[PDB]
Amino acid sequence: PNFSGNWKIIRSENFEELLKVLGVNVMLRKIAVAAASKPAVEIKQEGDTFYIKTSTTVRTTEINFKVGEEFEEQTVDGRPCKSLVKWESENKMVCEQKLLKGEGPKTSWTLELTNDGELIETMTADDVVCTKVFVRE
Image 1 (cartoon, helix red, strand yellow):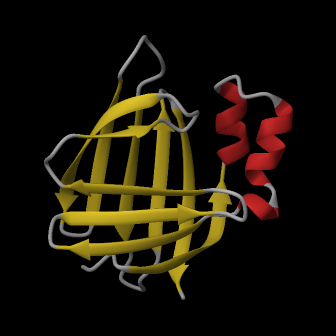
Image 2 (spheres, one colour):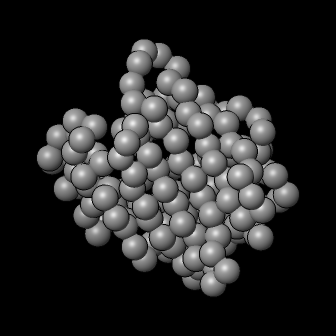
């Protein structure tokens, strides 16, 4: 169960629709799903410590966290949040997010490995879920 690698996206389901129900305007949705916005995800895992860099043709962001320790990131629609990841199993982590300011949808995400070595990401806002699948280069 090692999440490290250079992960390339191979499936995406319900992402634009999730943004739509969050109130994201149509220009930004279409951009978010364009080929040019396809995420490449680099992960370095060392036990419970993660470094994850997500890059597209125009953006790059890095997060560093340790499982069980609170950190700060942004929600699917860009609002700052405090996050905390826990293991649900040997091969799956789950993250609960809490907005830093104001109120909003209950948001969370998960990452898990398949035995064939696919990485599955889900992101949830209230009752709406999006799933992306990646494979290693």
